[PDB]
Length: 251
Length: 253
Image 1 (spheres, chains in turn brown, yellow):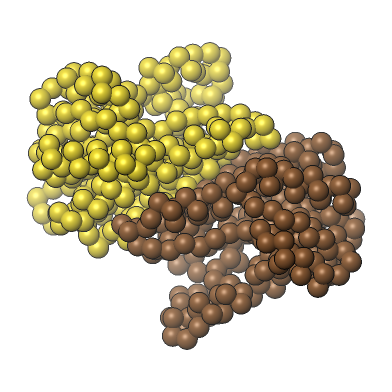
Image 2: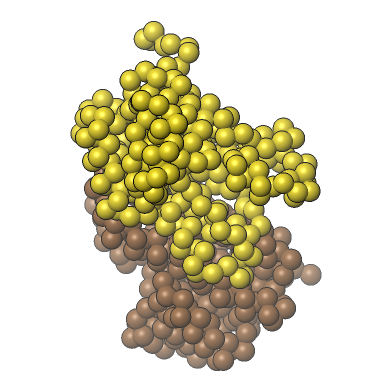
């Protein structure tokens, strides 16, 4: 029987980048749905503050997603604390923009190492855990509208996000046999505290003109999609890229 | 419309081809020479590049390039411009394949794949595009992707990540550089019967793979090269950001 309230009661979720922005909203949503949440972030202080805020079912873990050791140690620590991992969300991304003829190798490598390699390392470590446990699982990787369309100044970002989608689809293909659904979530511009700042004024008004919905997405809306994809209502959804873009990419 | 020559000549255009001394790069270099182009054969060693450029005759010249090194790539482009005066066409065909089950695949296989297939394509496309923008005469950039840039394939988690990435990257260069007359496209083959590929699919391995391809066979390097000639020509000036599958229909099912 599929419970159409989409409960997550007693499931254990990892959320990378979980202490701010989209990741904070996902952590909060998962807590509200009865899950245990491992809040993973590169800053121990930021993770500590977020997990304390979210209450007794949220615990902090330091994790540099670009580091295989840091990732493996975090996964081990989450298992030691909670017993198992049912859900993992990868929402540690970075954005480094410049015209394509100018963009530095540093901007390129940081983008690829964090957005693409980081998603690889976290997905592989969590998936190994899930395979060993034998109870299936859910992996949700944040991609972007930029995993579907080109955007000016986003050569590295688009490369990383298109890559995340191909990568995630391959994990989905190979891990169906283990009951692990692997999907991507692809937002348009999101009104995180940062995004509010970066898309204020006429710049934001101009961007909204091209979105059929006529506004940007809230982090809470991205988290609602994560809740659905993490649930028992989505067991036949795998390899999917769910766009939350207000129509941006369809024109 | 201009007179568009439906023989698709590349007379006096200068083309760089990475991985130009073997497999698909070698076939592309040979095709471009046959169409009248000057070809800069880039490969990882001086001897290998020299042997191909000698094979291809007086309009082909050799250059050493490790596409995963910014310095190597920049030096190669500078040397090509010194030798030929300009770059009109660049093809990135130096890719690598490292396969393993997704839960097992090493960070070494991941890095080698991303660094050559994706970062290498970025470095070459950026260096070539800079030269093209500066010269003001437009240009053509053709990046080899793969059927694996559209579909997942078991054991190909790093390969698919790199090839999806190449397409996204290439489409962004296309969007930004249309204003400078530079078309940037990808070519996405199924399995190709390079000297290597022949050895690699020699088995029932090959016969089973073919059952899933509507065309019922693999592609030859010369077929990939024919598509490259078309995309490098004046018959393709309105084609940019496109991914042209040469997959015998593999990906449509």
